[PDB]
Image (cartoon, coloured by chain):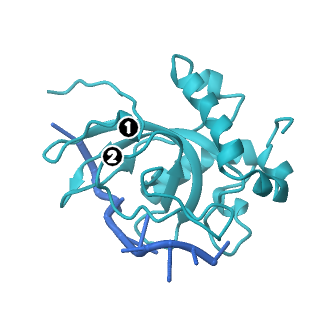
Chain colours: A cyan, B blue
Amino acid sequence: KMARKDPTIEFCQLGLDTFETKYITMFGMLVSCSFDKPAFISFVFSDFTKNDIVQNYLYDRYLIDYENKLELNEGFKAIMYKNQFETFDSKLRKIFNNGLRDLQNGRDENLSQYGIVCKMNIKVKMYNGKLNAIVRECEPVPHSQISSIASPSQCEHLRLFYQRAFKRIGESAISRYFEEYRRFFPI
DNA sequence: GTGTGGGTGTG
């Protein structure tokens, strides 16, 4: 028919299926990006839980440390038509006065030292057998908006994410850009 | 339940 709502899950809270398909909201921190493709700006987010779907390589979002990597069950790829990306970057330009392009140093496009935790509704489906997830929205969820974008359960889940990254992302890395990562928090 | 999955590494 023509009437559905927007559910929410997180890798482990998935539920898709081969012939299936649906919409879901994943919360996580951006770690990489690829605006070179003329079809969109490939993005790789990350958070807690563990993906159980087959998905694809999902790269490894080489954390700030280019020494080791992580599994493809912790991060995932996110995309959105450049127009959808502009609308998304616009939400960020208000928290950074600039677009993602203004965030990167001007060379590569992957970002994993700012965090930029945000929520986004994505449309998932099996592309030949893999989970093809796109991004329908892209609202930023730093700190002055989290309590205005989430609250019921999703709020603590978001708070629990910052606790993990603090010890998982590597305490030595936060020292390389402590001020850039602390955004507006007392580290 | 839409299209924009590329990769797969790591910068």
Q: Quadrant of residue A147?
A: top right
Residue wearing tag 1: A12
Disc sitting over residue A52 in the figure: 2
Residue A125: image x %, image y %?
24, 48
Q: Residue at x 65, y 48 (%)?
A: A168
Per the image, label 2 sits on a secondary structure element best described as loop
Disc 1, SS: helix
Q: Residues within 10 Å of mark 1 (few under 14, many from 20)?
A: some
In this view, the residue farthest toward the top is: A152
Who comes first in sequence, dot 1 or dot 2? 1
Mark number for residue A141?
Answer: none
The residue drawn where x is 49% and y is 62% is A41
Marks 1/2 in contact by CB < 8 Å: the verdict is yes
Q: Quadrant of residue A6?
A: top left
Would you say A175 lies left or right of A20 here?
right
| Residue at 57% over, 61% down | A32
Side of A30 relative to A107 (left or right): left
Image quadrant for the N terminus of chain A?
A: top left
Residue type pointed to by label 1: Cys
- Residue A142 versus residue A36 in the image, above or below: above
- Neighbours of disc 2 within 10 Å: few (<14), some (14-19), many (20+): some
The answer to whether A139 appears left or right of A100 in the picture is left
Q: Report, in whole angstroms, how far the alpha carbon at label 1 lies from the one at label 2.
A: 6 Å
Image location (x, y in percent) of residue A11: 39, 41
Depicted A129 relative to depicted A187: above or below: below
The chain to which mark 2 is attached is A
